[PDB]
Length: 287
Ligand SMILES: O[C@@H]1[C@H](O)[C@H](O)CO[C@H]1O
Ligand SMILES: [Ca+2]
Ligand SMILES: [Cl-]
Picture 1 (cartoon, rainbow, N blue to C red):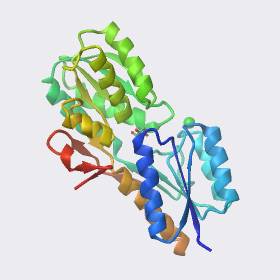
Picture 2 (picture 1 turned 60 degrees about the vertical axis):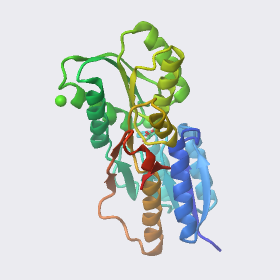
Picture 3 (picture 1 turned 90 degrees about the vertical axis):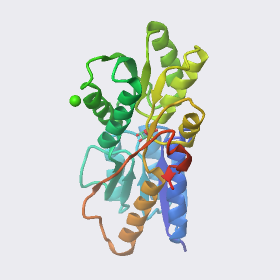
């Protein structure tokens, strides 16, 4: 009897994606839907399998945080041709008019906020390293660009390594160990996301370099807690919970009478998190 909404994200070991799934699930059930929550583990084939499952089960809409900007177009198009609309969150696909919605953070704006804080904490000088996200995710390059466009105004600041750790805490730890051995004179690390920042601060701490300034991106409870404890200095909040709920609200409107948002692509504002507002943050929302 109940209509079904399928929710598909990357693995829940990154709290960002878990929070999206829980937010979407909550809104779906609040509006009378049953839910089917699946993970694709950043694997396009697994994402294909999961969308087939949504189709097979008769989902009325799919909420998707995708497995690659290019690779995901065909999957979303498969669902579409099966008569099932997709409402994308967090990550864009490199196509318009396929998804009904793409509701993402303003990544360039956000990244600039975090870089501005990084520069301030750095006193406009010194050697730093950058950890970059997954090449398949347009968010990785957009954030890097925003960071670069701030930091390139400060000639005394110098990047001594720029490496991908693929949005992975464990990869970030290992990369940081190697980077730190090559570059003992680093003053700071700026990271494209919070799981990489957690890996970095762990590696720094284990090397006895607690003085190094780390700035992340996402606003997770884990990084909040680090900020509160004097670890990481700042992050940038993406409204993950609200974004997932908005996607479901749009899906429900569409299911009900084919209301579509005026603009497919929608941006949500980011907010800088630091010691002054970390205590107002919980599960990707400020109060
Ligand atoms: O926006 C998300 C989050 O930053 C996550 O932590 C990594 O993937 C990005 O696309
Ligand atoms: Ca500039
Ligand atoms: Cl891709």
